[PDB]
Each structure stands twice: as structure tokens, then as C-alpha cells.
Amino acid sequence: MLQPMAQALASLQGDDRVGVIEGRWIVFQPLAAPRSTGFIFYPGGRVDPRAYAPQARAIAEQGFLVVITPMPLNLAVFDADRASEVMAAFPEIEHWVIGGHSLGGAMAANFAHNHIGAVEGVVFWAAYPAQSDSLADRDDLTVYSIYGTLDGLATPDKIEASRALLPATARFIPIEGGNHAQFGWYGEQPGDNPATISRAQQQQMTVDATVEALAVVD
Amino acid sequence: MLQPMAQALASLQGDDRVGVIEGRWIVFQPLAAPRSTGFIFYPGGRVDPRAYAPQARAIAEQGFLVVITPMPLNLAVFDADRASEVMAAFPEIEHWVIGGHSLGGAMAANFAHNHIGAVEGVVFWAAYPAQSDSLADRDDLTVYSIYGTLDGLATPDKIEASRALLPATARFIPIEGGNHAQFGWYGEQPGDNPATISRAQQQQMTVDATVEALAVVD
Image 1 (tube, rainbow over the protein chains, first blue to last red):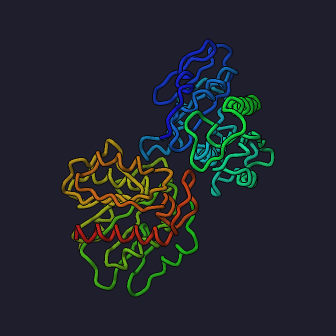
Image 2 (image 1 turned 90 degrees about the horizontal axis):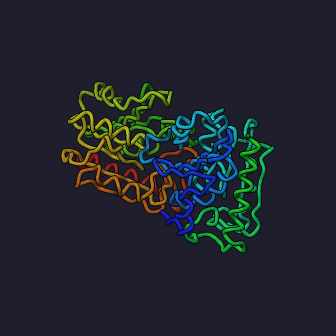
Image 3 (image 1 turned 135 degrees about the vertical axis):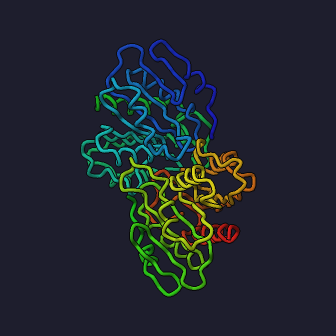
């Protein structure tokens, strides 16, 4: 898997507003006024889950539980539905949003498609549902699709065409100048284009848009 | 379930080389000169079993009985023991090989783990056993593991790690540019990558390797 950058590793530590637990999942617990909406996050395929610690920490600082949930060890753990065990572990959460980066987002869309009512929203980072996972008529769902306009792996053209698989009320959020790789803190990535905004700016906009989605659900 | 593509329906129509019976299983009976070895096949999770009919037919065309045995309609019931009932139905087959795609492959390993001497071989398509289903020192088994190098769900890194759970003599067969979905004729697969080879070339390579394995046991 693509390896976490130093700044990822620092994020795994507990600042004053956010506690972190590294176990079967990576858990980011708002220590202060915890909201009642949680975010289950699926990593990119072959990105080390730790690479997204800075994004998850920043989301939690705004009061939302974030559970980064690694790919299953075994194939019986379709339940892609590694989300259900997460939901068992935090019974106090009243509303679940799922999402992911890249292939992870596809997998999140898949869970949402196949388990009606187990989530209230889906957040994509540089991702889109498969043909078979259309959420086009799933009007119960709050859907956000955040994309980098310079992403070389999931181009804006492909993101935009995924409108026909998402509810009419889906919110598409352009990060102008952003790329595929800056949705986490790992390498550059083959296939991808150079960003014209720093990781810092790209993170911020990724965080603000995700938080908006979680707040809309909350 | 992910539905079979139109081609896959052509493969269910019996001729005078291969008779096909669709009942509780999909049975592909070679009528030419039948070999003494049978293949029991477990479908991938959520895939219509008929989606494998092209591969099963191509294998039966080379002499070997194939029986696709569906998992029960509900994802919540297991039954990896399914193969038992197939064996009861074909008393004249002398050697059994079990295999499957993805979750089907894992379930096949479970059956082989728990029914010692009921099969002499296991063939994985994009699959590997669970830890608790190790076939590590099962030198009685001919094991083939056929995998796509671009597979997004069961990645090459993951398949290679399953060496520890398989006999030393296991044969790993890489399908270069193959993905997860092209092990059958169904949609694109949620969570997968695009292949760089046609479904035909992937199918040809999956048939040849599986046939090679049945011939070995035979």
C-alpha cells in the first residue's frame, strides 16, 4: 500500500479536542461536544489507512466521530459491509454517514445501495458508484461528491457523469486545482496530475465540505 | 444479485457435446468422452450463478463435469457444505475438485478444510481461504490459485499472502491485466478496477488453468 507521510503520523496523536484509537479501526473521537452523526470512512485501494488521519482528525475537531475502516482481512467480510461492525461498536450514534476515497468511495456507495436505511448519507472523495449501485432514486440519502478538478485518475468528466447514478439533490463540490492524491497524505500517485493548490488548501476544502454533509445529516 | 450478461444465456442451452440441466444446480454434463473427475463450483457473493455458465461450459467441453451450486437466496445463511449433496448425486465420478470465485473460493476452502478426503483439489478464482480454513500442510490437495493482476478486491498482494494458507505445491496462475469481475459474465464489479484484457482472453486463461488442474487430479 502507499505509505503515510510524516504529517499523517503526527495526526494519530491526541490533540485536546480529539482522541485517537488505533485498533481494528482508526477511531477519532471528539472529546468535547460530540455530535450524534458518525462518519464511516473507507480508504483508497492500496492506500495505507493512516494516510487519511489528518483529514479524519480535522473532521473530528468539528464534533463528528470518524471511523477509518480498513479493507477486510477475509472475503467473508463483505459484511464492503465492514461498516456494520462499526455501527455495533458505537450504539449511541443516531445517524450514520458512509464515504470513502477512490475505490473506497465505490465500496461505500455499494454498502449504501445494498443496506437500505443503515446510512443517511454518502460522501465521495474522487469517487463514484458502480453502474449496478445506482442511488439515482435513493431520495432518503444526503449525497456529497467532492472532487479535484485536476485529478488525473478520476477526471471531472467522469465525476460529472456519475450524476446519473446519484439523487437529483446530490451536492457536487469542485476543489479547483486539487488532484486525486491530495485526498490523503501519501505519495504522489501514478496516473494523477500535479495540483496547483497545496495539500493544506485541498485538505481544508475536503474537510469543510464533509463537515457540511455531516451537519446536514445531523 | 448482479445479473448475467446476454452472452451467458447462450451457454445454458445444451447441445450434443455438453448437456445442461438447470435445477437445484446448474449441471454441465460432457456427453463426448466424460472424464472421471468432476468440478464443483461456488459462485461469488451476490452474483447470479448463471453468470459463470460460459466458463463452466468451456470446461465441460474439455471433458469434465461442472456443477454450479448456488448459495441460498439469503446472504445470512452459510452452507459451504453444499458440495456434499452434489457428490451424492454423481456416484460414478471418481475424483472431486471444488472451487469458486471470490467468496465462493473461500467457502470452497472451508469445505476442503472440514471434509478431509472428500475432494482431491481446490481451484480459486480471485480467492483465498480464511485463516481459520488454512490448507497449509494439506499435501493431499492439488491447489491452483488463478488471479487477475488488476483485481481491486482480492489484490495480487493479498493473493500472494495466501501462500501461507496453501500447500507448498500450490500453483499460482497470474492473469496479467485481468480483474475481479471477468471471472464471470455479469456487470462491472463494485470496488474493482478495469481490466486491460478482454473477457474472452481472461475466460480462456481461466478455463485452461482450471482444466489443467482437473487433468492433474484425474
